[PDB]
Image (spheres, rainbow, N blue to C red):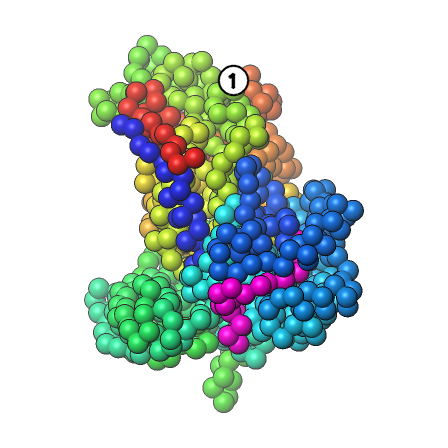
């Protein structure tokens, strides 16, 4: 089989994401830009369009990046003031783009009254571009040049505001920055254009010129101040952060307790037209544990466009306490012409708005439950402007799922609690989070897998398992203790077993393993496109937050469908994404390659990406599992967090990726969750992921990540602790066959501290995964051959 990867269709797919992911925040009709307008573009970052964040998910090599000025010229709908372009060009020869550990921003060119006045005299409209990047190992700081405007950027904005009566501000940013000073200066239009990959300027020009009507929505709540965010109190400590806000993350906090601290609510975004959402039929089916809600969205303005219907549930406070509203469903309309409408119907399972009882107060400890009382469903344009769709009342609690006490905090701390005041409004009070009473050593011992007796005369290939000819158990008996100790080691970076410049090879990492037809499976960064450290080019796609802002799983899936083929072309089997850690705080540096403060949106967008990658047999690796919500101190840092917050917020997106997304590969973190490293955490990697969610796949460490037993010293070679957790793969070693990290797999096995059954389980996970990859198909000679056309 031979498949064409059409590069022009790939471009168009990515461009569609850009034009659906831009978020228009304010506009007085200055957008869209009028046909034949002359635009003056301000901001030195105009010449170096941020196509991505920095670090592992920002090192995609490309031949060309289309920035905003070039996008606008290629549109043929406007022209750009060339004199001002040359002023920026000539100044930049003297003040070159700093490539660094790259800085968050570039120094702005100071502007004079003469430049700005002369620009306005020869143009119809000013566009001011403020650029920010961020990423791995540095957190975004609440200072000028990072989250705040620089003094010279502010001066630029004030001068342009004075001399132009039409002003447009664009935020070419990985994550949201302070809007207070920008809002005070009061431009005529404000749009967040994120970082759109290599064709970002094309999709951005589409929305600016009106060829596409913007339809992007915020995936985070924008508060007035950094200190309004509930997590700011407990964010940015390199050693330990207590997740005291608990389930009250983002709009779960603000809509419940602090509506007046919101500038822009979750799900907010506007269009060049206006829409009217009319609530429709509502039914509930308690026996099936679903409800069905309908509404109609009508374009009531004068230009075609899409809108998003967003559905929320208000649960009764009960004994647990609840956020006012939780997102349970959304649907983006087709393009609606003026005066036309679309009926949207959603069926919502009760598990979308259940609560995890981690205290026992409901009578069902360690369960997801719907407490007795009234459930009100809302629909609207955003969480704030969502209106009653229907209600139903439960006279008794319904247990949606029985789970276990898992990943519980090892120390007490106080968490936020919804308290219903005398009047009936909700205030924040605090309560003690109960401590874990789980016997961890016992749990491991009681659920120990059975050893498979070894048999080295067996000549079964991995091909014989794939065809159904033999059981995986029969095959795995062939692996020696050497083979077992070797197969749990990933080799990289730049292993010679796979495409050069990628992150890792795993599976067939010795002559012996490859002789059994276990192929070398290739892993590579990242969510926004293949990072090839050989210098080879690949498609640079929009950042994760831009993807999520589309509220459009279909457009995301379509784009990653092309990535699926591109990966096969490069013989990359595992793309190291989606990044899908919750936006707990706006200052986390890696927010650009994650999706949302909301777990449902997070899991739904992740799943769309995975479905895309699955189209032609490629795959993603969900990361970082879990609670890597802060870059500072991420090697040592301990996230202290309640079971409920884990179950409803931080794990929830990952759960969705497994059950809806078909996720079969996970990456753990550099850090600790509840007092041990995640790579050695049994509750995370076995109890929750496998035994409760039913995940069938592989777990790998983060690259050169530390591992420990609870209480013990962290090291980059405690592979025994890793295998005891069912974290299947240590990424990475320079030479896996030679044990170049000097790991303790065999010595622990020798001492009876690691059981061979545990190694065998990991080996089976690895082989089961490996045999369904395109690398196996290359051995079997039935892989897809890809040819790139259109270039
Ligand atoms: O590049 C391989 C890995 O490196 C680590 O530093 C990052 O945390 C991961 O996100 C990445 O996938």
| The quarter of the displayed image where residue 181 is located | bottom right
| Residue 229 in the image, given as x and y percentages of width and height | 60, 68
Q: Nearer the viewer, residue 738 or 81?
A: 81
Q: What residue is disc 1 on?
A: 737
Q: Residue at x 55, y 41 (%)?
A: 64
Q: Going by the image, does 542 lie left or right of 473?
A: right
Q: Going by the image, does 230 lie left or right of 113?
A: left
| Residue 727 in the image, given as x and y percentages of width and height | 47, 36
Q: Residue at x 38, y 75 (%)?
A: 302
Q: How many marks?
A: 1
Q: Which residues are magenta?
A: 24-45
Residue sitting farthest toward the bottom: 423
> For the residue labelled by badge 1, is the local secondary structure a helix, a strand or a loop?
loop
| Residue 544 in the image, given as x and y percentages of width and height | 49, 51
Q: Residue at x 56, y 59 (%)?
A: 79
Query: In this rendering, does residue 154 appear at all?
Result: no
Q: Nearer the viewer, residue 452 or 202?
A: 202
Q: Nearer the viewer, residue 593 or 567?
A: 567
| Residue 154 in the image, given as x and y percentages of width and height | 72, 66
Q: Mark 1: give few (<14), some (14-19) or many (20+) Cα within 10 Å.
A: many
| The quarter of the displayed image where residue 10 is located | top left
Residue sitting farthest toward the top: 457
Query: In this rendering, does residue 212 appear at all?
Result: yes
């Amino acid at each position: 089989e031979k498949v064409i990867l059409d590069w022009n269709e790939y471009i168009e797919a990515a461009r569609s994401v850009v034009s659906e992911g831009c978020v228009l925040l304010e506009n007085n009709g200055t957008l869209p830009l009028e046909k034949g307008a002359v635009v003056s573009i301000f901001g030195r970052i105009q010449t170096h369009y941020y196509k991505s964040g920095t670090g592992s998910g920002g090192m995609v090599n490309v031949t060309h990046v289309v920035g905003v000025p070039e996008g606008l010229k290629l549109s043929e709908h406007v022209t750009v003031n060339e004199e001002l372009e040359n002023i920026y060009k000539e100044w930049e020869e003297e003040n070159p783009f700093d490539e660094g550990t790259e800085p968050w921003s570039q120094p702005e060119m100071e502007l004079t009254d003469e430049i700005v006045s002369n620009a306005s005299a020869k143009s119809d409209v000013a566009i001011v571009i403020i650029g920010r990047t961020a990423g791995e190992d540095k957190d975004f700081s609440d200072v000028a040049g990072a989250y705040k405007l620089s003094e010279t950027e502010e001066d630029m904005l004030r001068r342009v505001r004075k001399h132009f009566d039409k002003m447009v501000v664009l935020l070419n940013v990985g994550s949201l920055m302070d809007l207070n000073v920008i809002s005070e200066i009061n431009p005529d239009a404000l749009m967040v254009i994120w970082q759109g990959g290599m064709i970002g300027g094309l999709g951005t020009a589409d929305v600016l010129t009106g060829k596409v009507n913007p339809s992007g929505k915020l995936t985070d709540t924008i508060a007035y101040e950094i200190n309004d965010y509930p997590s700011t109190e407990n964010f940015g400590d390199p050693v330990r952060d207590y997740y005291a806000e608990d389930i009250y993350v983002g709009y779960r906090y603000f809509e419940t307790f602090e509506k007046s601290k919101v500038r822009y609510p979750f799900g907010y975004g506007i269009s060049y037209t206006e829409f009217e959402h009319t609530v429709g039929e509502f039914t509930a089916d308690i026996n099936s544990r679903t409800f069905t809600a309908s509404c109609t969205v009508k374009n009531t303005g004068s230009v075609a466009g899409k809108d998003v219907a967003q559905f929320y549930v208000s649960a009764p406070q009960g004994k647990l306490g609840k956020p006012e509203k939780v997102l349970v469903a959304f649907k983006k309309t087709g393009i609606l012409n003026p005066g036309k409408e679309e009926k949207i119907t959603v069926t919502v399972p009760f598990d979308r708005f259940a609560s995890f009882d981690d205290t026992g107060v409901t009578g069902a400890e360690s369960c997801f439950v719907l407490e007795a009382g009234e459930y009100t469903v809302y629909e609207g344009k955003n969480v704030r402007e969502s209106y009653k769709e229907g209600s139903f009342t439960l006279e008794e609690n319904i247990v949606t799922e029985k789970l276990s006490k898992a990943l519980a905090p090892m120390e007490s701390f106080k968490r936020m609690k919804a308290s219903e005041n005398s009047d009936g409004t909700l205030s924040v009070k605090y309560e003690d989070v109960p401590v874990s009473d789980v016997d961890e050593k016992k749990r491991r011992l009681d659920n120990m897998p059975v050893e498979i007796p070894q048999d080295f005369t067996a000549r079964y290939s991995l091909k014989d398992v794939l065809s159904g000819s033999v059981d995986m158990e029969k095959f795995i008996a062939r692996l020696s203790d050497d083979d077992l100790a070797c197969i749990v080691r990933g080799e990289g970076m730049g292993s010679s077993l796979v495409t050069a410049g990628t992150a890792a090879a795993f599976g067939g990492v010795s002559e012996y393993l490859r002789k059994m037809d276990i192929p070398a499976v290739c892993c590579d960064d990242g969510p926004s496109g293949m990072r090839l450290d050989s210098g080879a080019t690949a498609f640079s796609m929009p950042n994760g937050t831009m993807l999520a802002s589309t509220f459009n799983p279909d457009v995301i899936e379509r784009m990653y469908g092309f990535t699926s083929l591109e990966m096969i072309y490069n013989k990359v089997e595992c793309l190291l994404g989606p990044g899908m850690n919750i936006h707990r705080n706006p200052l986390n540096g890696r927010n650009f390659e994650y999706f949302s403060e909301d777990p449902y949106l997070n899991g739904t967008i992740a799943s769309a990406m995975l479905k895309g990658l699955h189209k032609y047999g490629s795959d993603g690796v969900a990361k970082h599992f879990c609670c890597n919500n802060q870059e500072l101190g991420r090697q040592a840092c301990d996230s202290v967090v309640s079971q409920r917050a884990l179950r409803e917020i931080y794990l929830k997106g990952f759960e969705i990726a497994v059950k809806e997304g078909g996720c079969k590969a996970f990456m753990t973190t550099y850090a600790q969750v509840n007092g041990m490293w995640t790579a050695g955490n049994y509750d995370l990697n076995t109890r929750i992921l496998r035994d409760e969610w039913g995940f069938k796949g592989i777990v790998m460490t983060d690259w050169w990540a530390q591992v420990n037993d609870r209480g013990g010293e962290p090291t980059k070679n405690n592979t025994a602790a890793m295998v005891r957790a069912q974290n299947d793969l240590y990424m990475v070693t320079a030479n896996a066959a030679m044990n170049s990290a000097n790991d303790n797999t065999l010595s622990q096995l020798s001492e009876g501290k690691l059981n061979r059954a545990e190694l065998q389980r990991c080996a089976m996970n690895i082989c089961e995964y490996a045999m369904n990859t395109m690398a196996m198909k290359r051995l079997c000679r039935n892989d897809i051959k890809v040819e790139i056309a259109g270039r």
